[PDB]
Image (cartoon, rainbow, N blue to C red; front, top):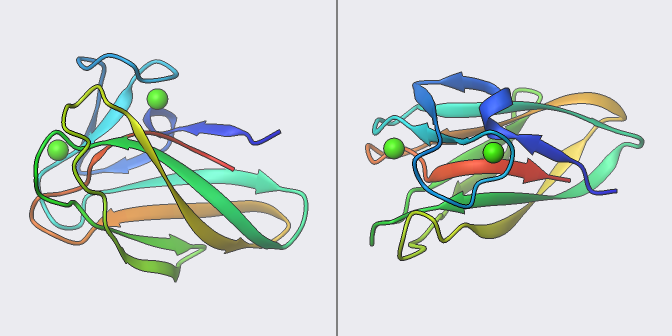
Amino acid sequence: DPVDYQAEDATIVQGAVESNHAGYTGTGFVNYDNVAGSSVEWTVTVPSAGTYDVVVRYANGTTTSRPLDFSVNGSISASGVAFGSTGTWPAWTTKTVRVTLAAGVNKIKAVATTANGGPNVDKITL
Ligand SMILES: [Ca+2]
Ligand SMILES: [Ca+2]
């Protein structure tokens, strides 16, 4: 139904696939490098054009938000989405971002806007 798209199987720019915090799904997660512009870009397929709720499963073991810009097929989707603390790195949490998609194959990209980089990201589901 909802379909999982694992971060570690996506296109990663300035990040690393890791597995040293428990509770991820798939074979690991992406640890964004601690730079602005680090990103993950998923290739997804949906049956019809329209709105989709993209459920981002992430962790942030710090008190500082790590915001992401989301874009869809190269156009901004959601700007400045905060990813706040989860207390600990294994405390994976979800946040929903609504992204407009075309029927069929689309790319969804989440890029870090601050020098902190992104939260750790397990997957998106939609
Ligand atoms: Ca990081
Ligand atoms: Ca994963």
